Image: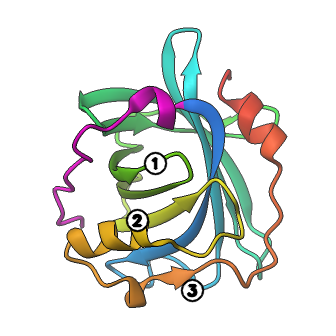
Amino acid sequence: ACTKNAIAQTGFNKDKYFNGDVWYVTDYLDLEPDDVPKRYCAALAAGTASGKLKEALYHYDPKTQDTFYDVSELQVESLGKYTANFKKVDKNGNVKVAVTAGNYYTFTVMYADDSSALIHTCLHKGNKDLGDLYAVLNRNKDAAAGDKVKSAVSAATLEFSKFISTKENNCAYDNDSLKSLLTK
């Protein structure tokens, strides 16, 4: 189960974050480890498509090769805090698992600037019991975390030394598919 009410960034700039471009996860913190594998790759695109707030997700396990994409419609709870359904799709947006009640995640942008961000997410999926996940994002898949986002980690009363990096997994991303999935 999740335990955190993450606080959104003061003065969060939604149009800058949701500008249609890709964000790479560079570092993550799972509060119930063994939720996820230690070695992992993830990225998303975030934007408005025909008036609708959307995210597209990509997950890849670099050892098992498990791979999946998702498309989500985001509903606003408050500035910087969203509830997102998800549908599992192939890379072209063809539906594999339809949207359903109880399959959703919350998404809070705790810090963002033009190049980096800190988010919290609470995933709900059927029967599963999942805990809080934090992620450090960058526009550059290889960027070491800078002082602005590391300070935000500290201000959230978290220790960046606890986060696991994704940078040594040889992850390669199809950014074109993530961008096109925003419309699907």
Circle nearer the N terminus (2, 1): 1
Residue furthest bottom as drawn: 161
Q: Position of residue 18 (x, y in %)?
A: 51, 32
In the image, which is nearer the foreground, mark 3 or mark 1? 1
| Residue 78 included in the magenta stretch of the image | no
Q: Which stretch is magenta?
A: 1-18
Q: Visible in this render: residue 94?
A: no
Q: Is residue 130 left or right of residue 22?
A: left
In the rendered structure, which disc, 3 or 2, sits on the residue that comes first in sequence? Answer: 3
Mark 3–mark 2 distance (CA, rounded to whole Å): 25 Å
Helix or strand or loop: what does disc 2 sit on? helix
In this rendering, is residue 99 above or below 125? above
Q: Nearer the viewer, residue 123 or 144?
A: 144
Residue type at mark 3 is Lys
Q: Quadrant of the N terminus?
A: bottom left
Asked if residue 10 is among those painted magenta in the image, a careful observer would answer yes
Q: Which residue is mark 1?
A: 113
Foreground residue among 54 and 35:
54
Q: Which residue is at a point 64% across and 83% down the rendered structure image?
A: 39
